[PDB]
Amino acid sequence: MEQSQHNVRLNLSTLYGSVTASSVVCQAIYKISATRFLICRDLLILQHLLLRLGDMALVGAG
Amino acid sequence: LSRGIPPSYPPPEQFYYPSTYNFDATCLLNSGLIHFACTGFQKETLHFLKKSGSSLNEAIPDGYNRCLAAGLLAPKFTDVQASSLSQEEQLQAILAAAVETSSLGLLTSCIKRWTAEEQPRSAANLRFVLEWTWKKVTLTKQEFDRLCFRLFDGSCNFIDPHTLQSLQQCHLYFSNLTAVLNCFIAQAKEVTQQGAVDLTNKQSVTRLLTLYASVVLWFCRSGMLPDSSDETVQLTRPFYNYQVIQQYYSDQRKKLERLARGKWDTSSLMIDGLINQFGDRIQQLWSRDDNGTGKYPPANL
Amino acid sequence: AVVKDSRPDQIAHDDKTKHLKAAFLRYCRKDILGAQSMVDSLFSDSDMEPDDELDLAVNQISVDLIDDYPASDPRWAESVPEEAAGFSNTSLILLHQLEDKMKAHSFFVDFLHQVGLFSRLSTCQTKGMLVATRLLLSEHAEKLSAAIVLKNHHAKLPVLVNSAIQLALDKRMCTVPQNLTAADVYFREVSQMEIIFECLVDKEEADLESTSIDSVEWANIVVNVNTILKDMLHVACQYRQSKN
């Protein structure tokens, strides 16, 4: 999505964008960035751990 | 209500005893709830010993006795009591078991604990465990060679899950002993320079075996043995056409020679220069293959 | 928390020795007050009476201190994980262990003087002959210095001294931990170092029977042993004279 304007269908297209909205959006993106950061790190750790475990209690690992 | 996980299926006889059943429960009253745990004695003893790991040796008798009584030890460790053993051999057996459990962390944490506070027999214990580690490396590499030779020759085309499990156990052992030696050099404040040199030599040996086990396991799991060009073992993965590729690069080499004549230095392949930096050691290594002696692609996997 | 009855040797003696060790560790940590408090907690220091039990406890504490490397010393440093083959300063570690042994003996003597127990030191029964325990501690220090200079000779003229060390070890049938060494064990229990002299002598006639004419070692060996033995006698004499 470049700065090519789309065809407006409501005035809700121009609605919202205030400084309060900016602050809320920045707080939310910070929070979700942190949460997804932790989640993805845990996912990679679990992936590597399960790959290294192999058949120690597992079956069908082929 | 649940049971523990084994380092290798099937579960031992300890799984079939109620002592393995660790379960928490809640009793309702007329004043509240009271919550308790059942058969946590084994982990209580284990964690007490580990927190006493800075002086673990003196508590090994009683702690090992408690673990045996709770059934935490493997079924084979129940036949020998801490009263008839000494703390050192008890610890060596525990360290061995941690190796087959693929638990290098227990050894690393225990040795780091021993590095602090006065404990004279810690040096003796680490010495004994290091020669034990090296001899275990030797036996594991010998056993791995015995498993892999029948596949290299081609006698066994498909191994069983048990052979695959044993190979995975050997690889995990290699990883754990790597970690043990690297920890050892990490908290080693003082060794002879010759000792450091040979310890680094043996750790490099462990790296070679670990990567070799990984790659050979990968070929076995992918079915690339005996060899990948074997059309009989290729039913799930791209097969290999040795003749086409080898003849193509032989023709490439001849074409390069004929173009170079005596006005160019370029008369060898890029892989040829690559092996040249390593010298003719690789030539002697590969001088047992058909379609050229030490010529890429070498015929032997 | 006193223990009833003195008697020659029982658990009360072990309790008294543990209390003496704790007071001595306080003195090493530089606390005269706690050491004196423990001393008063066992025996009044206002007494000038001869106390064979007190002297025996002091002597046993000294024996343990001189035959075992003291707490918190570099010998514990490689006892806790450092020893697989050893590092490059093992001889220095042994030397400084002897240094700390001398320092601890000095601290114990000063502790006894401070708490007034050195004055109460009267006698003990040794080999059928009575020795003042003050003299016993003096001899402990003298043979500790003898062990120090013996390690010096061990460094300077190694082959003969090590041959004598191993021969005396054979005659002594005492075990050696792998963390310790042969010289370390020999230098720890300084009570029996005398074996080394006659071991040297036996090796001396053994070699001199073989030695023939046109031999300079024929006299050099004797020169070396003469110097060494004179030196130990020298150091013992001077320590005794200085510390009387």
Image (spheres, coloured by chain):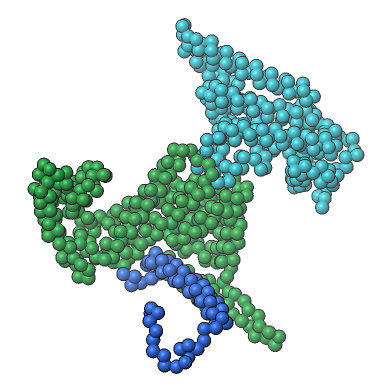
Chain colours: A blue, B green, C cyan
Image coordinates for residue C182, horizontal then vertical, percent: 55, 33
The residue closer to the viewer here, B70 or B123, is B123
Residue that appears at 42% across and 53% down: B178
Lateral position of residue C174 relative to residue B254, left or right = right
Res C231 → quadrant: top right
Image coordinates for residue C142, horizontal then vertical, percent: 71, 26
Q: How many marks?
A: 0
Image coordinates for residue B278, horizontal then vertical, percent: 26, 44
Residue C64: in sight, yes or no?
A: yes
The residue closer to the viewer here, B282 or C133, is B282
Toward the right, the furthest residue is: C46
Residue that appears at 38% across and 79% down: A1
Res C131 → quadrant: top right
Lateral position of residue B100 relative to residue B227, left or right = right
Toward the bottom, the furthest residue is: A10
Res B245 → quadrant: bottom left
Residue C52: in sight, yes or no?
A: no
Toward the top, the furthest residue is: C213
The relative height of residue A34 versus residue C228 in the rendered view (above or below) is: below
Quadrant where the C terminus of chain B sits is bottom left
Residue that appears at 37% across and 58% down: B170
The relative height of residue B57 versus residue C203 in the rendered view (above or below) is: below
Image coordinates for residue A23, horizontal then vertical, percent: 56, 78
Residue that appears at 55% across and 83% down: A18
The residue closer to the viewer here, C143 or B104, is B104
The residue closer to the viewer here, C239 or B13, is C239
